[PDB]
Amino acid sequence: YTPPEGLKKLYASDFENSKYPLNIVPSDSVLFAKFLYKAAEEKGNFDNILSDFQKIAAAASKLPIFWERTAVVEKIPEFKQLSEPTFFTLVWMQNNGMLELIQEVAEVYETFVNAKQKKAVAKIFVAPGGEKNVEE
Amino acid sequence: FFKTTEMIGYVHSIDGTIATLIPAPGNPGVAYNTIIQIQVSPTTFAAGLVFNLEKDGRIGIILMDNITEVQSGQKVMATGQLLHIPVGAGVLGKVVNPLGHE
Amino acid sequence: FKTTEMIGYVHSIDGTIATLIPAPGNPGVAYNTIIQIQVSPTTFAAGLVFNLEKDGRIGIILMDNITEVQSGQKVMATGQLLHIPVGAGVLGKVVNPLGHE
Amino acid sequence: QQRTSSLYNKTRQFGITAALIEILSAMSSLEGNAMKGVRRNKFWEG
Image (cartoon, rainbow over all chains, first blue to last red; front, side, top):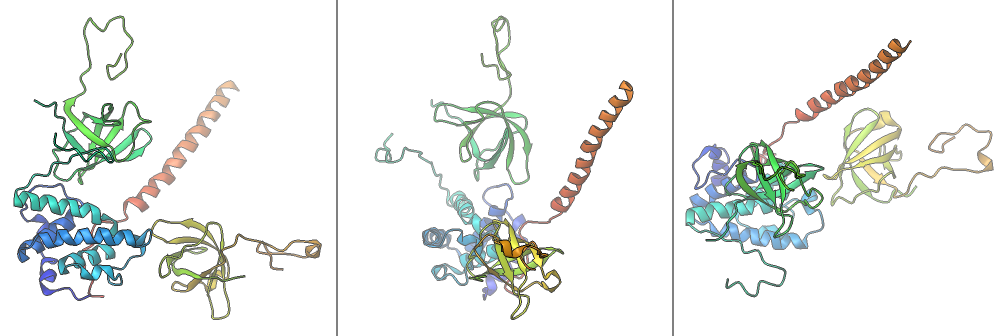
């Protein structure tokens, strides 16, 4: 892998102690979200990384069962379309053996963006097939 | 005027009677020695006692009732109060449990 | 012995036991089955699968040629439980638990 | 005889209790001293 010089510098700083929109308790899935947020913030485009996660999830369904145990994002063909900051994190996760936290990381990254973008997401829990009527 | 509750997280592990809760990112949070209510069903709940607040936000619950109906991935609400039980003279002559239920 | 497929590479050798990191694509072995560690180009050790872990690492009880087992060697699998020779022809002989005389 | 058989039983129970603890305190050191987290390394540099 050839990390871009920009990601190399952020990966060296103590971004974990930087200021963020919300004070979320430290966690393994939170460290990556903080990293991606800071990298995205410098580039100024938060949405792209969010969109990439949606393709990571779609690709995952096609990958073999228990792919996270044997996966090498470098070798996987689908993950080539992901953004540079997004692909860097996946390799970083793989070396640390934490590729199963992708789903957890995505939610946190959205929360930080929503806090910065000032959006409030309301979860409407409905029965399977009962989502037709949500007027109430 | 809704009867809003306070969701804190989701059940993660159930090791017999003890259990663990994973926080929902950016949710209110829970206190120590307080009583939490795991939503076994949209209308029914099971009681637990907070025993350990961890560095990662994971909560350590001791389950009390309906422990067979507790399943991982169930939402947990917070009362925000230490266990208060019904007491007085209206409870005399009755058989109750530690949670105050008759 | 059908050394069907390579299932991993030796990673740890704690005396008479071993661990195997998975081969390309985590082929996966069965439990309580026999594996053959390629100690030499034309010689093999033997081991019994004892632990199948989530990471894909496989715990092995070494059974022979323990002093020739080194980390990095390939591990073929047999896919069969342990079968030993039996019959009237095995009477009056000293036999190994693996069936060898 | 009854006073000594009582102490023998009390000594073969305390023995098993206190021995299993010793072997299970070491199991926690060899397990609780398995450092983990998110290792910060130049993983590309390898």
